[PDB]
Amino acid sequence: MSEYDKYSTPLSSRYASEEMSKIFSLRNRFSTWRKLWLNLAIAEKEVGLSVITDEAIEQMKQHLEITDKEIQDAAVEEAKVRHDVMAHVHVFGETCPSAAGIIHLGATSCFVTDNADLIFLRDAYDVLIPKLVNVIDRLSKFALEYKDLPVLGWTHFQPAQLTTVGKRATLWLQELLWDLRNMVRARNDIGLRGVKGTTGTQASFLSLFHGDHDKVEELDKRVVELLGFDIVYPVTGQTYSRKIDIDVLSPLASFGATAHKFATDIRLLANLKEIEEPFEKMAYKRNPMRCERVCSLARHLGGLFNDAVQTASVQWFERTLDDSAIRRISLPSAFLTVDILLSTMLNITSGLVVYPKVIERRINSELPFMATENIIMAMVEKGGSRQDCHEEIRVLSHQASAVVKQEGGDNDLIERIKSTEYFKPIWNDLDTLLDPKTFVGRAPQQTEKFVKNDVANALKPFEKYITTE
Amino acid sequence: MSEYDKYSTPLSSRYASEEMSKIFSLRNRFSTWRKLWLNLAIAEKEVGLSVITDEAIEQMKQHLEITDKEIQDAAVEEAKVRHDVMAHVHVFGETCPSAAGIIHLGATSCFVTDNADLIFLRDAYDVLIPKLVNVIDRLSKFALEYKDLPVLGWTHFQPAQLTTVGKRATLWLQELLWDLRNMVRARNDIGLRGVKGTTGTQASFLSLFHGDHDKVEELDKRVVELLGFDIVYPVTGQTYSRKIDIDVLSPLASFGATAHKFATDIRLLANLKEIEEPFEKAMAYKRNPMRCERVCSLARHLGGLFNDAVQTASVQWFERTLDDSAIRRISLPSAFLTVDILLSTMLNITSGLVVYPKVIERRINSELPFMATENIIMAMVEKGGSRQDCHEEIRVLSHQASAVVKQEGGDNDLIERIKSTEYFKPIWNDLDTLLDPKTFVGRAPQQTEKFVKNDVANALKPFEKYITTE
Ligand SMILES: [Ca+2]
Ligand SMILES: [Ca+2]
Ligand SMILES: [Cl-]
Ligand SMILES: [Cl-]
Ligand SMILES: [Cl-]
Ligand SMILES: [Cl-]
Ligand SMILES: [Cl-]
Ligand SMILES: [Cl-]
Ligand SMILES: [Cl-]
Ligand SMILES: [Cl-]
Ligand SMILES: [Mg+2]
Ligand SMILES: [Mg+2]
């Protein structure tokens, strides 16, 4: 029946995420079960189960990538036996008649379903992490380029001591370095369930090796090694602990806050006309639509993390099946969401448009109200009284403030100072006392050091993933 | 106003957590500010601000612990000058008159409020982690003790292939090892904001050192070193990134699931009469797993506190917005107090779990015959009989016995039916020793022993000094 007549999620269709979506597709699901069956037979034969023939293994080797027809045949078999794994065991054994006898030998259902999911989780991180690396790369190049450009600081979203455009971008950069840290940890923490049997005791395999514990341990480690994993969980019930889904998702939940804060900030800078999203195809009014989408999708990750926390919390004993439906939603959705976020942020950070003039206009309007201490010191320096000067400025500041709020014209405080005889000693020093570059503290130095050290050191292990456009 | 007449959070007035609650007390907040001012003064002197005097440093050193009188005098000033920190600078400098021109020199208010918060986060983790270590220690001793004891397994909470009591405990232990990993990471990831100025640019410290960047950098490094921290955040706005609060709470959120799953399993085992919570004070027949119920209750509360942190960081505009202040005042203390109560309670539970082997064994005996079909068939095949015939014969008796159990409420009589059926005569004398639960536990005892003596032992080795006895 028609796709136009059924709901489809956007993590899937509307936004380009072809590779990530493939990892969580049905074809990759069933193909990965076959890869697991192949390597279960290889390892079992090696460890000593002579019932497995090399010819069975060689057949399975040519049929790891399930075809549309086999999927449909497995669907027919599933509605008959009401078990998707056993349906695929049957169809795989039809395709590979020399292997029909030994496919799934000794294993329980979760041998293929659970190990496949753990494979997908690590494969998914290996898609995400190259994208995050490139976001860090493009934004830090941005930060360095603009390290010297003074910009109005904002606290409570009210005018605050000057920083620089590049320095502000290091805030977003620092959060993304913590994301690289969190994601790399989670990625390299993942192990495989291996062969564990129905309640984790490996009773079935112990029997198949006639009570030889060493053989069972050799099998468990070998099959995981063949799948390219270093870690096999030694103690499980039927399933890998669903607490692993929490710790796999916590870096995604944390990253959501990074993305939402970055995108919110840019949306405000777009309102201020200081920074806009990249040109895409010259309009006066432009919407920061990519950042609004980043906020939208980032916000969705919190509930998926709670899905995982609540699921693990009520897994009774060696497992309950109330993990199954929700995991088919929460795990793909979370990685697809972050995949879309990172690709969008990569598009945004590749071509941020800066308007230094708008930036300078805004600074000019606000800085005189923040330059009181400079005006005071400069007059004391010239022999004036400090409080006498502190009172004279407050008079002019209130007048300027009234002109801004009370009347609506441009801040005229500097003009007022040039018109007040008291301040004559500094009339030719007001350009210097109001020079924005003198107000940005260490913001340029902080930025250069952070890009050149923190960011470079963090990205050095992933240099091979850094691309261009 | 009387304390009986106002709401008090049970996280500080109902459960034992003196130490953790003191970390988040008013006195420790204001005393930590003073500790921050003392080391700010020491660091500024070493880097070259002679305006502060050696006498001031020594006088601040025996007034770091604020008195109730000073707290009260700081409160009379906070109402007057509309600001807590300045009010405490004043009182500290009245209490310490040779440091009064020197306290807070060059710093902004977040130098004390924000650095103190980070100190409390790591100090709080240093309270939690030793309790976690000891929970792991007691429960792993339990798992080893019961590594051999066969127990009905449960999937879908229906009878499943036998495991052992100790092996089941290794599921909880493995989760706790991940909690140790997560918490130790978060604990050691924490740095200090240091001295950063109102927007993170250190403009006022750069001005105070007449433009010497190296002195600003070395001041930032040294004040943080004096407080016992190796990491100083190089790039901030007004404050440390609130994303740090998320990454400090995510191990606590994850641990909430460990605690809830552990305590839910024990409450089910208590229903089954297999395992009960420790005796307190002629034992009562019926006992409630009330400590486990409390663990589930408080564990559940951690999820919302983590969401507090996620959403807070998400909407921090630019160099800071002050919608982080009130909520962080709830979420950070509540989360560490909740996990502290959870660990104390779990330590008490796991120190004296009560196991009833004959209830466990009675349950296995009633279920194992239905699970031993293949074993009975293999026994007949090994006498020389037919797998197909034996399969059908046992299928008939199994359905009769199932009907007795469910339709009649009777004891499972499958074994008696077998011994009563002429077809099964070749295996009559094999049934008793066949149905031996010790032969059905697979590798559960060996898995348990290896896990405790390798994975657990290795995880706890760096923390041996924290292991205590009762
Ligand atoms: Ca071959
Ligand atoms: Ca051995
Ligand atoms: Cl195909
Ligand atoms: Cl098994
Ligand atoms: Cl298995
Ligand atoms: Cl065996
Ligand atoms: Cl959209
Ligand atoms: Cl500061
Ligand atoms: Cl400053
Ligand atoms: Cl309670
Ligand atoms: Mg001039
Ligand atoms: Mg009876």
Image (tube, coloured by chain):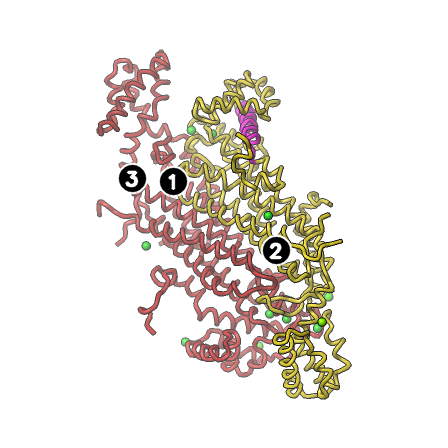
Chain colours: A red, B yellow
- Give the residue number, with chain letter if any, for mark 3: A272
- Looking at the rendered structure, the kind of residue marked 3 is Leu
Magenta: main secondary structure equals helix
- Chain holding disc 1: B
Q: Which residues are magenta?
A: B24-45
Q: Are marks 1 and 2 in contact (CB under 8 Å)?
A: no
Q: Are marks 3 and 1 in contact (CB under 8 Å)?
A: no
Look at the image and tell me whether residue B24 can be seen: yes
**Residue at 44% over, 39% down:** B324
Tag 2 secondary structure: helix
Tag 3 secondary structure: loop
Crowdedness near tag 2: few (<14), some (14–19) or many (≥20) residues, C-alpha within 10 Å: many
- Give the residue number, with chain letter if any, for mark 1: B317
Residue A190 spot, x, y in % from top left:
55, 58
Closer to us: mark 1 or mark 2?
2
With respect to residue A33, does B93 lie above or below?
above
Spatial separation of the CA atoms under disc 2 and disc 3: 52 Å
Q: Quadrant of ligand 4?
A: bottom right
- Marker disc for residue B262: 2
